Length: 309
Ligand SMILES: OC[C@H]1O[C@@H](O[C@H]2[C@H](O)[C@H](O)[C@H](O[C@H]3[C@H](O)[C@H](O)[C@H](O[C@H]4[C@H](O)[C@H](O)[C@H](O)O[C@@H]4CO)O[C@@H]3CO)O[C@@H]2CO)[C@@H](O)[C@@H](O)[C@@H]1O
Ligand SMILES: *[C@@H]1O[C@H](CO)[C@@H](O)[C@H](O)[C@H]1NC(C)=O
Ligand SMILES: *[C@@H]1O[C@H](CO)[C@@H](O)[C@H](O)[C@H]1NC(C)=O
Ligand SMILES: *[C@@H]1O[C@H](CO)[C@@H](O)[C@H](O)[C@H]1NC(C)=O
Ligand SMILES: *[C@@H]1O[C@H](CO)[C@@H](O)[C@H](O)[C@H]1NC(C)=O
Image 1 (cartoon, rainbow, N blue to C red):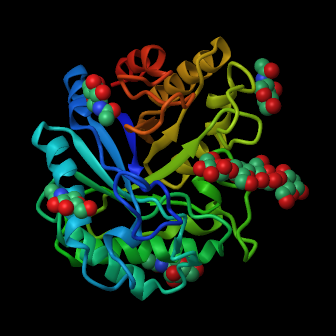
Image 2: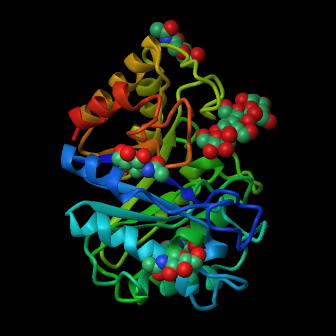
């Protein structure tokens, strides 16, 4: 169903706010995403920095310039009939502080969603990879985001909710927040007036699930790492999307990736698709880059992504 790529770059140099366009961060290569769309890819997760989109205070107005760049890339993707997911890539933090005010987060999402409220090909993603946080707070922030999105009149779009502990699928039931609570203990009770919640988890295939190593543990490690989360989703009648995953260019990773995507296809009653990490124009020889012109992983995994589209 959903099959596509992350676009990463507009959130780079996150320590430099607002940062310098062309030095700290950049926006995306529409010629490259046009190739992906022409191939049949139908979703692009557009990563961005909260402090650049809504500077100084998360309840404030949106920066016209950075919003203007976001909107051009969103409209490029959606004018060509693909989904654009808007992802504040902030780990649950704003100017480095854990986001502790559900009211402020509701307001931030009301503001952002208001700019895209009539575009049904837009998807909202409450925040990338909350971590190191009270589990209850992460659930409460996801709920606040849903509230603000629908309060803006953005009623057609899926809302991607992300768990604590880097929203890892393999640790959904085991990783503990600051309050001792797991994602399984906190994220089930989310409600949406439009019933369009996607449980958005990430899954890497290396030893510690971080994706920093090119070595995938073994040929089945992806599917096996989704099994516990898939039971939680099936049992609690939720649906999900694999919003980041990757393997490097070697035979074990390629088999593990194939096997993961087959597992999601076999469990399509709960898994709606998968989004590769990552494309974007500033990755160079990054082992996971599928950017067409120079991504080391493009020629191996671009066909695999399309095979599950
Ligand atoms: O995944 C993308 C995202 O990953 C980030 O790195 C994470 C990584 O995802 C993963 O969550 C990893 O989790 C470890 C964790 O570090 C603990 O060490 C944990 O261990 C525990 C051990 O299993 C025992 O239970 C013991 O009793 O307690 C130990 C911890 O106290 O095991 C978890 C997985 O099993 O943590 C890293 C970050 O440290 C980032 O790389 C991020 O940038 C990336 O986007
Ligand atoms: C943008 O994508 C095109 C098409 O793949 C590529 O030829 C070009 O080099 C890319 N530009 C940048 C800055 O990466
Ligand atoms: C993108 O941002 C720059 C400032 O960094 C601004 O000059 C430009 O007009 C923006 N683009 C759009 C389409 O608004
Ligand atoms: C979810 O549970 C928490 C506390 O357990 C709280 O935010 C609220 O009571 C619940 N949310 C909804 C929408 O019921
Ligand atoms: C793959 O690795 C996981 C985690 O280390 C392990 O539990 C599992 O037994 C391994 N599978 C095979 C077939 O070796």
